[PDB]
Image (tube, coloured by chain):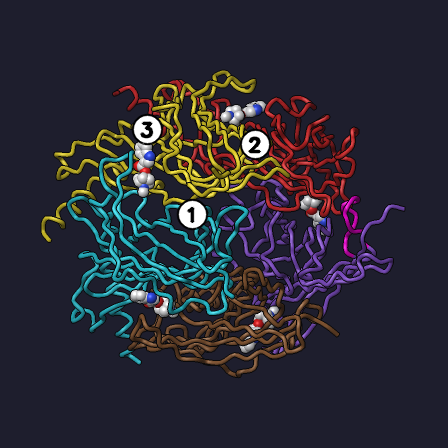
Chain colours: A brown, B purple, C cyan, D red, E yellow
């Protein structure tokens, strides 16, 4: 009974991975749109001696590849499966103003659905460039960090959000810092280096030292 | 004789691991219950500048797979064996409010028994979100951290505990912090992101600074 | 959708032909020397530690070189003119900070852009602690420090370096840094060491900076 | 020159026969138990942190055991009596500090010595933080602490431990340490846990130390 | 174009001939012993912590040895006399600090230079924390500390060591370090241990240093 479902799932993964060579990533002729979102859990530290702030959050990443679709009826009605992020292509979404390598807090496992879509939710701790002047005031401090592909232009990787409101409903209630507001907004960057635009989602956080 | 038992173990492992492929993990039609329990060894530090607390504890993980069963009589009466956690599938049990990657303090080796049960006991150090206010009072401070699958819903991984009492019999007797109470409780919740419930075990610790008499 | 499928097979075939149908490039020799263009984009001076004389910089290191072994005719691969690939898939130059005090910490994906003429562009973002006395940083005149970059093991007969400009790119310098940049230059130098009879090449990064006020 | 060629050939053949022809030792069993000889050489107490009750030791661990599967006749292999090999080529015991607070940091190469009677010698140098209250370190009496080392997953029925002496080797203890050693002993102990019907064996390192005067 | 193509081919063939056509060198033995020439270049004393008696040093080690198994005739390979290769491609000696307090942090690419006579030059740069009491560092006489380097697992019957000079290279020492070096020596020694029937060889690096002053 369960033997058959296990066999079917193995067969599906072999047909998708071991049979077909890995996705070479997007191109101008085969571009990809990645949906990004942020769930802020904690501002751990705001360092005014170096202007770095440490955030704990997760990143919702979603995209769709035709090379990952399958007919459930042809695979025991399996409609999704979990797999190691190392078995699939994942986008190179990067903070543009980190000061330390990102520290990964969640399992590098993703969910693949029969329509070819992938959902990958990396939890992480990030130190980024942030002047916390005003954090000890009622108006608070405002910092910002952009997330995008490091190496793919908007012709290969476009980004989008499902909303411009950051999810603060999991934010730690006894953090040293309360969040006043947090937005997440698509932007188009034209850097002086590079003819091709680079797309990003800009996370803007207004925050202050917790005071009743 | 011992040469034989050694060959029997090598055979069993070859049969279990190298014959059928890796267990692809649970599915809604083949769901798995993971039994979780905690053994708290030390509250190492409570940082009020950041509201992070560092715990040293073990996490008892137990589950059972049909694909790991064998007949002991077909293998020289071997009833269990130890093996690298890399040789088997393991659940993606994750602290939901960690602030640093968890640091593993013990060997990544599991015990597999002939009924297909796996016992895995990783010791580790965790920093998590905790406001230690009141730690210097008679009432002490209270913090909590949930643990569960990151990627699997309750329809794929369920959790349970064998007791609601955290195991304190190995708690370091000269810690800077004394434990007032430690409980572990199964919870079910919905997140706005997904239509399925997710299961966690919530570790709640009440603690205060040790004082001399 | 077949056209998207075709474009993918073209890319998969090109990489297969460049990488898997030949052994990696063995690096440069006296007979086939390489020129690496180096350029720096200063993002932030994060920290200036006067107790240890170390300064920490966040910057991109632009690296560019060209190999005949990476050339292809786009017309034979459906007009594919460039592609992105893991820096592990190709040879990369061993460009090293000569006065680092800690291992460089990499902040961006290790992915390069390869073009049909055989040119490679690799732009790693990095945090570097290097040797620097920040005395004067809290004055109008400010502090001056310098760090040299070059091959560790190739002399100027095998790896030559150049810059496209002597001016460090400051267009991405963090506007609310603790430190403002008075000037930042990048200059090719040639050195002889006592060890070795051949000259080594480096690019010297000189940065003048002061506490923002 | 030719003879060195023969010697190298003989060693490569031995290693190939021991490692590539037969599978790796699956570890000890109830029917084929193993005794590991364990001893400690304490080099330094680096740090004692009274705010977290963690002490940091630098030491080496002497580990020795013997496997029939690693035996060979020297006459079959050009009179070779022993060799050095990566610890990855062989099974090693999962000897673990029961009260560490951070992952152990390895200071020496992961290479072991294998002798023709199947005995193995492995001497990992390490830095360990462990649970220790340094109260009294600033007195003439000093402070005492203890840390036990044993297998994480094998009971006394699979791995037994022994010591050649109960005296910790202090002959390489750093003479200018912040802490002088008053005593250091290593004692086999048998412990029962409520979790487990089988006892586990450990070597308990007890150190008495004080601030150098 | 065609001259460069050819030289690349010769090098590719040489490396294949050295690495794939025989298994990787099993290291030295009593019958096939090796001498490593060792030397130190000190770049910076970054930190001297008197709360724990640890000093942090950035330096590089010059390591040289020679193997018959890495020899070739340049005339057979387009007159190639040397090449650069990943240190993972070759055996390297397990030269270890005897009194480190933290793992070494590597600051240079792990690549060595191989020459047709079978000699290997490997120059690992690193930051080392080692056991060192800095008392007297705030005085004219300074502080003196020492750290030995040698093989961890091979005795003198398998790995011998030599220096080219007793004078540590201080020419590249960081001129604006918090600490000035008064002197640095590097001396071969023989150590006998109770564990083992034969002695182990080390180079003892002795450094006299003090807080930088003026005038
Ligand atoms: C997301 N991106 C990061 C920064 C901009 C965009 C693309 C990559 O940067 C570049 O290509 C260059 C930067 N500076 C340069 C100078 C000469 C050539 C290229 C670049 C990585
Ligand atoms: C234990 N889990 C963590 C958080 C909830 C549950 C499942 C995983 O989260 C998601 O799938 C999403 C979170 N936020 C989202 C937003 C849009 C789509 C998916 C998600 C990882
Ligand atoms: C950029 N480089 C670093 C330092 C100089 C140049 C080449 C490499 O060093 C050497 O080969 C030697 C240094 N000191 C030595 C002493 C004896 C033999 C060789 C060397 C690495
Ligand atoms: C050295 N060892 C460490 C601790 C005891 C011995 C064996 C391992 O622990 C267990 O199996 C359990 C601990 N607590 C438990 C609770 C339920 C089931 C098993 C255990 C790891
Ligand atoms: C450089 N070396 C370090 C220390 C001496 C030499 C060889 C290695 O040590 C041993 O084998 C033992 C030390 N102490 C012991 C006690 C019983 C058995 C072996 C050893 C590592």
Q: Distance between the residues labelled 1 and 2?
A: 28 Å
Do callouts 1 and 2 point to residues on the same chain? no
Instruction: Indicate which label's residue lies in the foreground, 1 or 3.
Output: 1
- Label 3: which residue? E65
Query: Which residues are the magenta region?
Result: B166-179
Mark 2 or mark 3, earlier in chain: 3
Residue B170 colored in magenta in the image: yes
Residue C208 placement (x, y as % from top left):
41, 57
Q: Distance between the residues labelled 2 and 3?
A: 41 Å
Label number found at residue E139: 2
Residue behind label 3 places its C-beta within 8 angstroms of ligand 3: no
Chain for mark 3? E
Mark 3 packing: few (<14 Cα in 10 Å), some, or many (20+)?
some
Q: Residue at x 78, y 29 (%)?
A: D140
A43 left or right of E209? right
Write down the quadrant of residue E66 in the picture: top left
Label number found at residue C100: 1
Residue behind label 1 places its C-beta within 8 angstroms of ligand 3: no
Position of C84 relative to D3 (above/below):
below
A21 left or right of C43? left
Instruction: Indicate which label's residue lies in the foreground, 2 or 3.
Output: 2
Instruction: Indicate which label's residue lies in the foreground, 1 or 2.
Output: 2
Q: Look at the magenta stretch and give its main secondary structure.
A: loop
What secondary structure is marked by label 2? loop
């Amino acid at each position: 009974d369960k033997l058959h479902s296990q066999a079917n799932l193995m067969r599906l993964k072999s047909d998708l991975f071991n049979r077909s060579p890995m996705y070479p990533g997007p191109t101008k002729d085969d571009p990809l749109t990645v949906t990004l979102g942020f769930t802020l859990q904690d501002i751990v530290k705001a360092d005014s001696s170096t202007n770095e702030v440490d955030l704990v959050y997760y990143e919702q990443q979603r995209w769709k590849l035709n090379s990952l679709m399958w007919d459930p009826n042809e695979y025991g009605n399996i409609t999704d499966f979990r797999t190691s992020a190392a078995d699939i292509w994942t986008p190179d979404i990067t903070a543009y103003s980190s000061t330390r390598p990102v520290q990964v807090l969640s399992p590098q496992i993703a969910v693949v659905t029969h329509d070819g879509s992938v959902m990958f939710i990396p939890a992480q701790r990030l130190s980024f460039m942030c002047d916390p002047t005003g954090v000890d005031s009622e108006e608070g401090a405002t910092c910002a960090v952009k997330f995008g592909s490091w190496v793919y232009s908007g012709f290969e990787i476009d980004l989008k959000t499902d909303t411009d409101q950051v999810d603060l409903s999991s934010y730690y209630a006894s953090s040293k810092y309360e969040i006043l507001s947090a937005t997440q907004t698509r932007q188009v960057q034209h850097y002086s280096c590079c003819p091709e635009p680079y797309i990003d989602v800009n996370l803007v956080v207004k925050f202050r030292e917790r005071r009743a």
